[PDB]
Image (cartoon, rainbow, N blue to C red):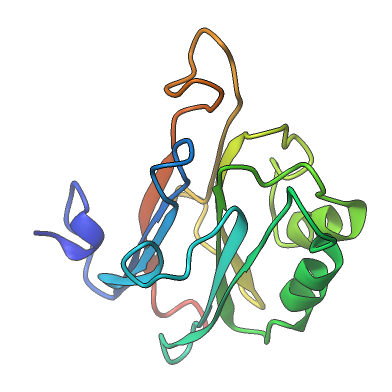
Length: 177
């Protein structure tokens, strides 16, 4: 019904977003922006690791979508360079699927922490994580921009994985007016 199937309607001059981490291996991570799925099963571009959607804040257009596997390969470096290359006045949306920490290295953690992440250095194996960043401007303090959920045997929604987490909000379009 509502933009990105939001619980409450967004205020007028705002960009709607909904970020969903993966829930175990069968429930996929999803990035929704302005009622359009940027990353997800639907668009066939979601995978294990850290999934990043980059949007031009000024035009509201998707500029890039890329995933980086943190269980295999050496994708931490290519992820840090992808994040660092992002142009100013960009929105960055980051979600975990399955695992985003095994091979997660310092350079990548520093590039994400530079964007305002308080949880990227607390990432544990299979912790579910969702994050909204702005490059070249500040997001309002009121919007939910980050969440982390660690694997815990008593709380785990799946055998071996924590429950998926979500953040939904409305970003005002005039932060650079």
